[PDB]
Image (cartoon, rainbow, N blue to C red; front, side, top):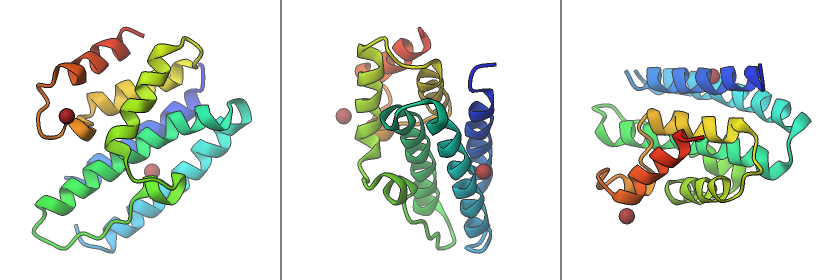
Length: 152
Ligand SMILES: [Br-]
Ligand SMILES: [Br-]
């Protein structure tokens, strides 16, 4: 039952996202608000156990996943979608499509990390996080990251 409560929160965010995705700017704003409440509890709970770096490794990719799906909806949507980046509000950077795979390199290189690090990456990747690979999901490194992460 390792970090079960954290996992549920990450699932919930994935849900609040995949739902925003299947709507006007007052709905979006309410769900974003929920997401931010869920992030607050996720951080508070992880930081009782884990260093700041480990907490970031688990929460940044989830934010980058949410940002990516929202930016894509905002690209493909009939209505005007407004979305300030979560990854930027929380972690002061906006290069998530690259930095997630930098995180993934790190957790894959050293066998020091809690299992939730790998599960969080596995989840966003099973939910079609592409990041820097958006233009071509046939990329061999992209497929290797998936294979290697699930092997954990
Ligand atoms: Br949520
Ligand atoms: Br590339």
